[PDB]
Amino acid sequence: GARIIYDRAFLMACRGGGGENLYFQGKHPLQNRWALWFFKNDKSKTWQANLRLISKFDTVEDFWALYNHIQLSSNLMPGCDYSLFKDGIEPMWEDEKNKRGGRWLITLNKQQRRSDLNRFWLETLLCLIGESFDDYSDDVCGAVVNVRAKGDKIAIWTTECENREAVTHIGRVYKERLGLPPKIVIGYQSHADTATKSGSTTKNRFVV
Amino acid sequence: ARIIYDRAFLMACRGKHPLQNRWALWFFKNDKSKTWQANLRLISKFDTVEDFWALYNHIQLSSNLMPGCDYSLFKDGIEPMWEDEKNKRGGRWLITLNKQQRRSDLNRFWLETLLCLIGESFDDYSDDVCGAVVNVRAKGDKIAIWTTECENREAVTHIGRVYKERLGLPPKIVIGYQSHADTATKSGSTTKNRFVV
Ligand SMILES: CC[C@@H](O[C@H](C)CO)c1ccc(-c2ccccc2F)cc1NCCO
Ligand SMILES: CC[C@@H](O[C@H](C)CO)c1ccc(-c2ccccc2F)cc1NCCO
Image (cartoon, rainbow over all chains, first blue to last red; front, top):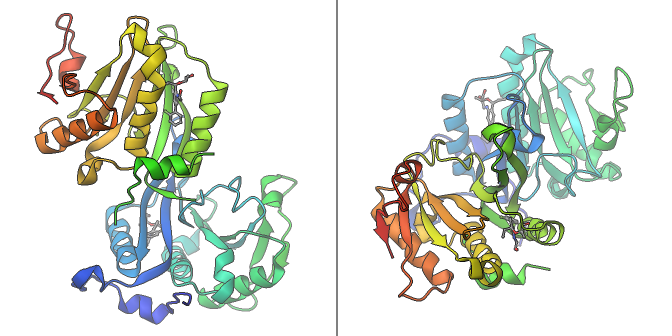
């Protein structure tokens, strides 16, 4: 009665349609159901009005259908954010599953939009849907991409910043899967520190 | 697979269970010194049974009934205005309540409407549902389910028959479906009903 885990190679092989899905039993179930959110930035609107749920999915094939659809139907607008979160967790730090939590953060420079945004974001998505952090995948809430003019942010959000073992294992595996050099250190920030603006930086509770 | 909750399951969850859709609760007062942008205020969004009940229990305790007001629950991304792309070709099953039935049936009928929406009570035809509107008025209240396409007769009349069943209305009491394009034009004391159940 075990966790459903997909490595990167298996998820890539399941890409590009193909499956007949006979008996509604030929699709590959995910451990969790996931919801894709969009948060727009315009028209003098409340935080709630700008957050929109796009779509939910709980198979590898339906992930790839949505991915292929967004990849062909959507263009990149700064001010926007996309978030993939487990079903029942809103992509806001005030949520019961995020308020005690935080994020592993990747910051991309202006150059790296064109070179690394799509690659790093896909690798992040596969880490989530594939349950890549072993038992510590349960600490994962979701992932956020902030598209910005200064430079783009990609983050894995986790549920509890005081779970050092879980947080640091997520961190180490994520950095490995992004193929980041050991010189490039990524930082974990409590959402409670990120919420308070106190200077040019937020404190990192952990680094890998 | 579609997430469907019957009435009994949703009531059992009242003091997390995902909804098929995310829903947005809107409030609208008729005020001309402010116009349709400032009058229409978003109150809150939700996509679980428990968060529906938290908001319901909150509004039920914290809010008192003012005529001229309207509340609307619509799917996330559909504004509660007929000009919206998802409503302009559509219409509404309308329940009109007399002055007496404000005290007896408003809260009951409105709750039953809400459960039909969040529970996906119309089978595949729940996708034709946009939302629901309650207009609190002195003449007598209005409750309506809004659907996306008035030319989908099969979708529309299934919704109306299930809705009428869930309101526990007698078969003598016939409800009417009105195109938003007919309701927009004031032509007398009544609007034409494209269908009736
Ligand atoms: C920031 C990348 C953004 O780019 C779009 C093409 C618009 O610029 C984007 C957003 C969401 C998803 C997404 C799809 C399926 C499941 C979860 C998801 F988050 C994928 C992408 N991009 C893929 C590569 O283009
Ligand atoms: C019956 C109209 C109004 O009644 C109050 C007395 C108004 O001050 C009302 C409005 C919205 C909601 C509502 C709550 C949660 C989600 C969607 C909703 F539309 C519930 C109610 N009434 C509850 C039962 O009386």
